[PDB]
Length: 353
DNA sequence: AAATTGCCGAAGACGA
DNA sequence: TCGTCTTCGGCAATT
Ligand SMILES: [Zn+2]
Image (cartoon, rainbow, N blue to C red; front, top):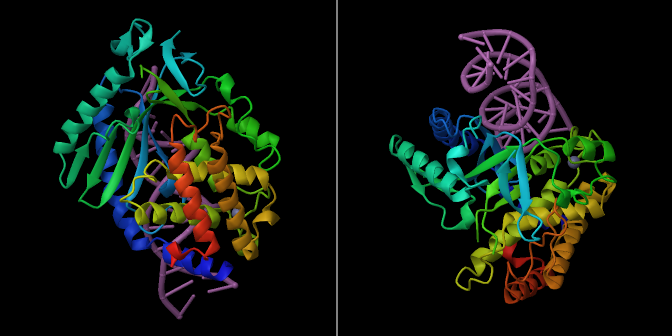
């Protein structure tokens, strides 16, 4: 119900004072790390790309989780697709002229060699600061590479990335289906921007996975079919509101069933990816009228349920990369989430209060 | 030679 | 329903 849902969105609004505090802590530590990394021959060309919910303005409840990408401008990359996985590649170069040659294993760029020096440099620099601790972010395949905890309150996931300015790989050719929503001219402009490669095992070599975090952020902050969508109060859509509610639904279910582990692998990236597909299905701003919040939220819920039931959630940029494949998420986990979402919807989402 | 810096203003919280 | 205030993405000017 649009009124229950509005009340939920109000309780989810971030406090401006907390934003100021958290951003001050995060920026101070991040600036410290970039300064250090720029002094190193290997990470000379590093730069900051802020990613994810906080910088997309769909962070809910508290600004206590930040995603950060340290991207390296590298000479022209030559990619070799790993197996036929569409998203995972070996990185080669087209060595005297490049500072990453210390990480070559033959012609192949070693993600783990690069990750190891990156983590070592950050871990040493984090001891040089106070109220900040490193954790080597589990496996994660390598991305994020490290997780910082600042004064036991704010988490910073740091991802190492390579920036390529070459044309996007062929597996993206049919992705980013925004032509009838954001326009063909905007799709052409986005695909002229760089793409990123982050260190990531495929189910286990020296592979990198394609990343488009910067495009996802650009779409979210310029998200209407109308150029003026959300710029003035009389043209406010409920797109970001629906994404926030989807994220809260998943977060609340993962907390509710934290002792059962079925929901551990579902992520905000899944919810955001599904949301972009609903945007492609509903391209007009009038299909996201603020008066229709309950209806629009239900489109998001329904599409997400169809993804779970069919075990199919395409990466928005790489359509043959299935985020919900059996290899990645057990059927029983998808089944359990379906059951709980259907229950919640049938009972006016008790998990929201 | 090329990485750093300061400024702009849109986005979004918030109080009258 | 407004003005106000703070943060962040981009880049010319700076160094
Ligand atoms: Zn809008």
